[PDB]
Length: 288
Length: 50
Image 1 (cartoon, rainbow over the protein chains, first blue to last red):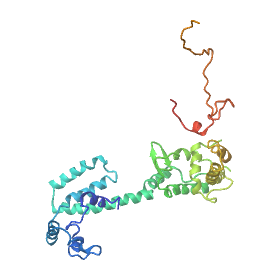
Image 2 (cartoon, rainbow over the protein chains, first blue to last red; image 1 turned 135 degrees about the vertical axis):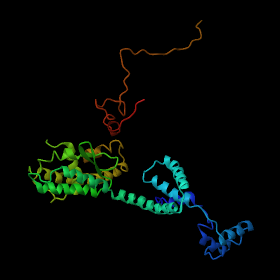
Image 3 (cartoon, chains in turn purple, orange; image 1 turned 180 degrees about the horizontal axis):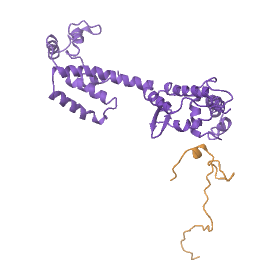
Image 4 (cartoon, each protein chain N blue to C red; image 1 turned 180 degrees about the vertical axis):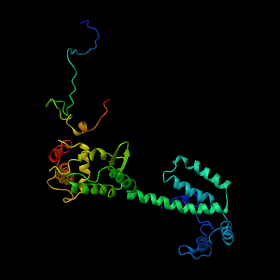
């Protein structure tokens, strides 16, 4: 609701109190004293405050939804990055001017259809961010059209590797693939390091799938990122690519338990009393 | 017995030398590669010197 463009439009246009137009039932429960908490809080008002609320209740005042319907649209354009936040007042007066030149019963109905349409489109984008798959599956499958589907040797290792390659981009919503000129790439996160080169890695691994000092370090970076998404039976045991994928799974598991060992040794080296400079260097040389 | 009222001017001259300030935690030469040059603060991070 904090990211809802019509809840945010109600927090910027609608009053923060109980008027007798937007909240007719909640103020008639208070005029007629049938409220659970403090029923007699309306009898204790002056006639200027008490009779002016009765008149707005038995014959309520009409209002314009047009500034509220447009502000729900502007606050969804500013949320789906269609406009800048600095342009939020520029396009608000630009849209209010257009629905004033062309105001009709059709347009006010069409703004009522479009404020339900932008509630969906804000939520559809925020679902697509947390899923994180649609921008990557169409560009990884576009990569794999370029790569051949039949290697000469080790096709069993190759078709499970590229199936685990689809498992990184699916089971990590921040990861993405794209193109920049000839080659394609893979970032493990938005605005993060460890960017592998897919067109350079698969022109390096091609010719190494059945071999059983020769690897480019981005191919080894690819074999490090693909390692937690690869089973022991996904690739072979004797194959040099399969021998490394088991070796990189042990390196991740050792770096996962040297992380917990680091948090234990440095915790009991401060309380026991050591140099804080040398507690942090002798621990790494014990763990690396 | 007729000495004037005097003030003392002190100074030193130390020619031929360079004023060494060693980058060590106790200003001592315990080795050519000092203990602060090996420090993870000074060997992994980039610091400004002013």
